[PDB]
Image (cartoon, rainbow, N blue to C red):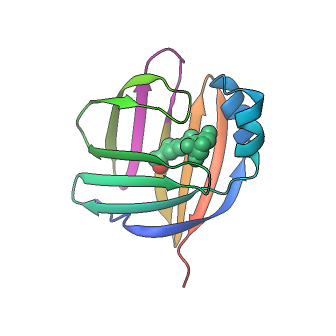
Amino acid sequence: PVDFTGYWKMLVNENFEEYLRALDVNVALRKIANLLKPDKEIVQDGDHMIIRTLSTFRNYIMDFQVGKEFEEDLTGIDDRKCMTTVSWDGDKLQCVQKGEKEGRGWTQWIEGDELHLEMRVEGVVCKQVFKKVQ
Ligand SMILES: CC1=C(/C=C/C(C)=C/C=C/C(C)=C/CO)C(C)(C)CCC1
């Protein structure tokens, strides 16, 4: 497939508040989250991927094998646990996070020189777009 490795800076973040509200994040944390601009630092070797979502407040780290289900600990976000699987769909990554909230997951892909991420939960869609600094 494709190599997502890079330090990607956020350009776009649409509907993040609604996405966090659907995860039951409290108003205090939503307030500070509202002014963050999380970046993505990704290192990949084939199906082995580390995706670090980096902000000045808190980071969220994923470390997984594409195609292999794992127990995802969402401490720092909503502090839930999911049965999560990230899969290749051509050159896109499709993530399903099974657990309390229905329809939770995300899709990540590169379009030209932009990293696109669509995060989903209970019918809410949050759109994020990132670019490396040339
Ligand atoms: C609310 C909240 C945050 C949410 C991070 C999320 C929702 C990351 C999702 C990452 C994905 C889907 C990576 C695969 O690209 C972070 C922890 C930044 C700071 C503390 C507040």
Residue 63 percent location from the top left of the image? 31, 46
Residue at image position (46%, 56%) is 109
Residue 46 percent location from the top left of the image? 21, 59
Residue 92 is covered by the magenta coloring? yes
- Res 66 quadrant in image: top left
**Image height of 92 relative to 19, above or below:** below
Where ligand 1 lies, by image quadrant?
top right
Residue at image position (33%, 53%) is 50
Viewed as shown, does residue 22 lie left or right of 66?
Answer: right
Viewed as shown, does residue 30 lie left or right of 96?
Answer: right
Residue 90 percent location from the top left of the image? 34, 51
**Image height of 80 relative to 19, above or below:** above
Viewed as shown, does residue 20 lie left or right of 43?
Answer: right
Residue 106 percent location from the top left of the image? 50, 39
Q: Nearer the viewer, residue 53 or 65?
A: 53
Q: State the residue lying farthest toward the top.
A: 100
**Image height of 83 relative to 1, above or below:** above
Q: State the residue lying farthest toward the bottom.
A: 134
Q: Nearer the viewer, residue 16 or 36?
A: 36
Screen quadrant of the N terminus? bottom left
Screen quadrant of the C terminus? bottom right
Numbered disc total: 0
Q: Nearer the viewer, residue 4 or 37?
A: 37
Q: Report the span colored magenta.
A: 91-105
Viewed as shown, does residue 106 lie left or right of 35?
Answer: left
- Res 56 quadrant in image: bottom right
Residue at image position (47%, 69%) is 7
